[PDB]
Amino acid sequence: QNVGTQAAEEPLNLPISVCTAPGNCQTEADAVVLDSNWRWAHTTTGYTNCYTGNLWDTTLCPTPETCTTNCAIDGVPLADWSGTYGGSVTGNKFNLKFVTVSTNIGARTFLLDSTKTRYRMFQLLNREFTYDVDVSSLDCGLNGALYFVSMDADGGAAKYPTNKGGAKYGTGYCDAQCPHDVKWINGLANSKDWTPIPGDANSGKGYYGNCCAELDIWEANKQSQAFTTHPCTPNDQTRCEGVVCGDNDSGDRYNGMCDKDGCDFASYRMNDHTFYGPGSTFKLDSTKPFTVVSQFITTDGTDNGDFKEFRRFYVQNGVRIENSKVNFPGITAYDSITDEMCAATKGLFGDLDDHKNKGGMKQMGEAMRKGMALVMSIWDDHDVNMLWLDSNYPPTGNPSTPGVARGPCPTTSGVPSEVEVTQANAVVSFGNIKFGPIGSTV
Image 1 (cartoon, rainbow, N blue to C red):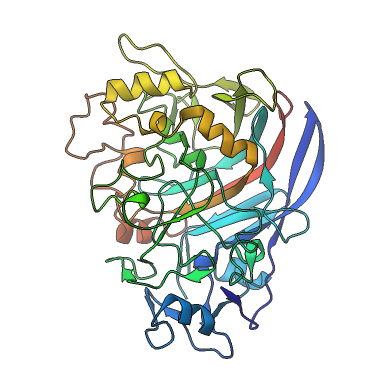
Image 2: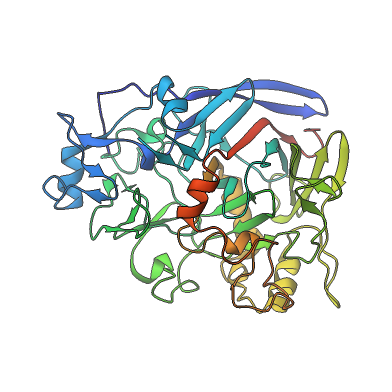
């Protein structure tokens, strides 16, 4: 995309901590940038929309190349962050409102480095990543997500010279779902064969998808939470078409370059329904804030080893809370993501181990070694109504069959039109982000 001249781009300042030992950290003066999908797209030498509602203008965008020549994405000024997009920062806390009323629904954002010209790339192997979260106002059907993806640090600017904005304009998004709803891919409008998504007034799908590796630290609302590894072959940003995208709609979910299911550790799905929930007698009380700690263990305990284990623990009101465990007869009580856990649990659930097909923890680790961009988002799910996270999936499945039940939400929950009314004022908060060696962040 070209860059427009109507509004300066002003990312929100967000300090994080880089740590060397427990309680010995230094501030890193980073910032938050809005994903290019949420930006106004208009004519390069005017005010005329190139995209309105869920459609590209066919006169301006008869082809992707012409669209890209004629159109530009514009900046987010400071005033518009809260007023238009529902984003705000207080000290080291970042807040994202779900619906902001001209009416904005959801948000996806990235962490910029201290220069505000590149994404802050995190080399996560043999490191610990930690943050405080509040998901108390997110119920069934919503997801306040924090995760990493194998985006380029410059959003693709060096690879795709028609991308003028780079990381500064939140470009280059890709993930392990190979999404077609990304409006700008490889420096070009994804306007070919663009199709609105029914019941989604703001979104559509273009000819291409954009694939890359994804490490989900946090997919969650107050009812259920998960962390998940998604390797791809290769891991780096890859524009896809046809079978390579692994499109759900053509029966290709397991035929593409990315592991779409991922290998998940989701406490409720692993059959501990009392670990996490909205109340003081759950082990971890989702009505109150808490700290989420993630440790990425290698084979030799060094930065050069292969990724072998994703460990997790929590801190809430000064109380250390170890992760829940897998709880099925004849299955080891795993409390972390490893290749063995993935094989054993997917075996039990009858899920295809595409994680293993894509190179497993080792391949996931190669993405983490090269460095990944931090994503913070809030969203509802127009495909599957978040049932995969917090309900029975498939909805018609027996909840006593291992793998089906992922949370207590009813199978009628999560319809975007309903959650966008009922949960309009939901806000996820991510704060006090800390990064360092294992054992350094609490």
